[PDB]
Image (tube, rainbow, N blue to C red; front, top):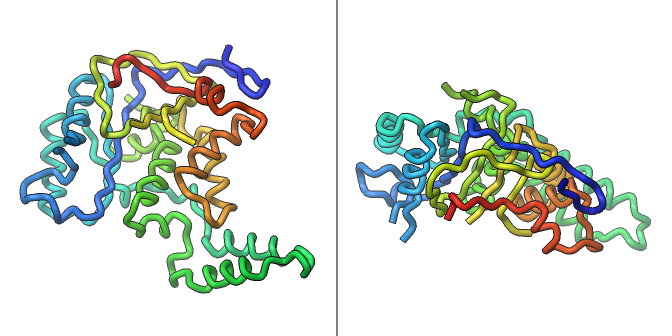
Length: 279
């Protein structure tokens, strides 16, 4: 049985019923010519990979979590794609309930402000405290929300933050639209990946495996997997908190009790996600 940091874990299976999830967060949808689904499809055949995956895995649902200021015409191009390939679900980030994961931005800053203020004045770190208080004061009115603050960003931490939250939701991300249980896992794939014939059943230590760093893939055997909740917990306590490096990497590392005493190549070997069907 799989083991790491001295502790043993079961190799949990991920059903052939498990949905597959892609993500496309588009900061300039107005660059796409009229009549095209606003997913990059050049050199980078992301829209083709997604369509191909839904072709191959005919017994699964292939979701694409999308976000960006898409026009009426682009939204109708999405519905046309759903109507062609009838196992592709286009899920808009703004229609998803993420409320169970949120936390006020002010409480994250306040908890860190209080932590720094509790050191004796000779060690206090007043420059950091000045940076923290300025961030607390500049929280926009009515947007005192960890999730809302990432919803309005438009660079790659926008994508990264909601990738983590989508995999937390896993099966429940699909069922809360309109087969799959809210408690089932998901297979998250980067859009640059090509499936070459079906995946079958997957196996993951403690129900999670990843092909990512700390061509990505994350697989979980259930929603609200504890290794992703560990990363959420860092997003809720650490002001800097990068969604990828902290919300994904450090979280999964902390869940498995990884430390500087361990070998990253051993950890990687232990958590790795590989399949011969995925190029």
